[PDB]
Amino acid sequence: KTIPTFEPKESILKKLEDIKPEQVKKQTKLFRIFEPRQLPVYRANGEKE
Amino acid sequence: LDNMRKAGLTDIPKMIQDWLVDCSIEKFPLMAKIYSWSFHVGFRKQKMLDAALDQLKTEYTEDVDDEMYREY
């Protein structure tokens, strides 16, 4: 029998003694935003090295 | 009452018909008497299957509200 599927949000709870405090962040790699990269280069007049 | 006459009933629609002329409560116990004459005919002891299918007909639809069921 094709039932529906009625899904409320159910708002999963805890109580205060069951609140886990925190887990500290120790650092992974250093969070780079830039990195070097090889590219070709072209002398003035436009042509190549 | 048209279904009632269609079943083969003659006197008891007339008894139900002459009361509506006044709609009085003094003649009304007849109706009450009539309402008890219906349940002293017996049970409708049909099959488990067909008796379940009085209940097991379902029309479940994705057209009902959602505003209603969440509040419910």
Image: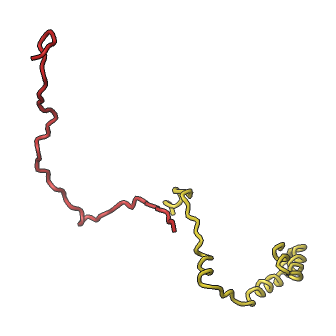
Chain colours: A red, B yellow
Q: Position of residue A38 (x, y in %)?
A: 11, 27
The residue most toward the left is: A49
Residue at 11 percent across and 50 percent down: it is A26
Q: How many marks?
A: 0
Quadrant of the image for the C terminus of chain A? top left
Residue at 62 percent across and 76 percent down: it is B54
The residue most toward the top is: A45
Residue at 81 percent across and 74 percent down: it is B3
Q: Position of residue A34 (x, y in %)?
A: 15, 32
Q: Is residue A39 left or right of residue B2?
A: left
Q: Is residue A43 above or below residue A28?
A: above
Q: Is residue B72 above or below residue A28?
A: below
Q: Is residue A20 left or right of residue A8?
A: left
Q: Is residue A48 above or below residue A2?
A: above
Q: Position of residue B24 (x, y in %)?
A: 86, 76
Camera-side residue: A43 or B27? A43
Camera-side residue: A43 or B37? A43
Camera-side residue: A27 or B49? B49
Q: Is residue A33 left or right of residue B61?
A: left
Instruction: State which quadrant residue A22 falls in.
Output: bottom left
Q: Position of residue B47 (x, y in %)?
A: 62, 85
The residue most toward the front is: A48
Q: Is residue A15 left or right of residue B27?
A: left
